[PDB]
Image (spheres, helix red, strand yellow):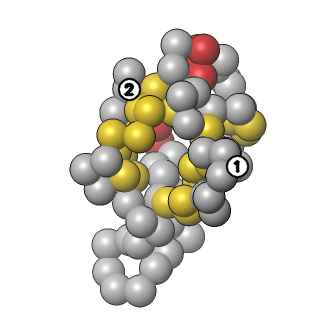
Amino acid sequence: MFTINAEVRKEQGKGASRRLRAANKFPAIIYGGKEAPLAIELDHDKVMNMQAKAEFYSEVLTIVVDGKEIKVKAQDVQRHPYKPKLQHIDFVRA
């Protein structure tokens, strides 16, 4: 449903993860149920709009992994309402 932006664990620069640990992003993981899961980038601020509280996973959602509209429901959405944290998100295929 939603449009959560994501990239293959790579930030604005070269290599990997040379911006998130200063700006306001954190990595997240997408599981399916067979193959090894896909570790990807995730914003903190931008996604909070979608997160809100429980609703995020309830109505189902979609992640754009470099022009791949991966539909997820998610399970361990380790978010914090009221005051944001967004420690990690373990998404799961819809």
For the residues marked 2 and 1, what is the alpha-carbon distance in whole angstroms?
Answer: 20 Å
Disc tally is 2
Q: Residue furthest front?
A: 34
Q: Residue 42: percent from the left, percent from the top?
A: 48, 52
- Examine the rendering and report whether any part of residue 24 can be seen: no
Q: Secondary structure at mark 2?
A: loop
Q: Which residue occupies 38% across, 26% down?
A: 2
Q: Which residue is mark 2?
A: 2
- Examine the rendering and report whether any part of residue 14 can be seen: yes
Q: Is residue 66 above or below residue 16?
A: above
- Identify which amino acid the numbered label 1 is placed on: Gln
Q: Evaluate if marks 2 and 1 touch, with contact meaning CB atoms under 8 Å apart.
A: no
The image quadrant where one finds the N terminus is top left
Q: Residue 49: percent from the left, percent from the top?
A: 45, 27
Q: Tell me the crowding category of disc 2: few under 14, some 14 to 19, or many 20 or more residues within 10 angstroms, Cα based.
A: some
Q: Is residue 71 above or below residue 86?
A: above
Q: Is residue 36 above or below residue 79?
A: below
Closer to us: mark 2 or mark 1?
2
| In the image: residue 75, left or right of residue 70 | right
Quick one: label 2 or label 1, which is nearer the N terminus?
A: 2
Q: Which residue occupies 34% across, 33% down?
A: 3
Judge by depth and name the residue closer to the eye, 25 or 71.
71
| In the image: residue 32, left or right of residue 64 | right
- Identify which amino acid the numbered label 2 is placed on: Phe
Q: Tell me the crowding category of disc 1: few under 14, some 14 to 19, or many 20 or more residues within 10 angstroms, Cα based.
A: few
Task: Specify the label residue 87 is tagged with.
Answer: 1
Judge by depth and name the residue closer to the eye, 53 or 36.
36
Q: Is residue 74 above or below residue 39?
A: above
The image quadrant where one finds the C terminus is top right
Task: Specify the label residue 3 is tagged with.
Answer: none
Judge by depth and name the residue closer to the eye, 60 or 15.
60
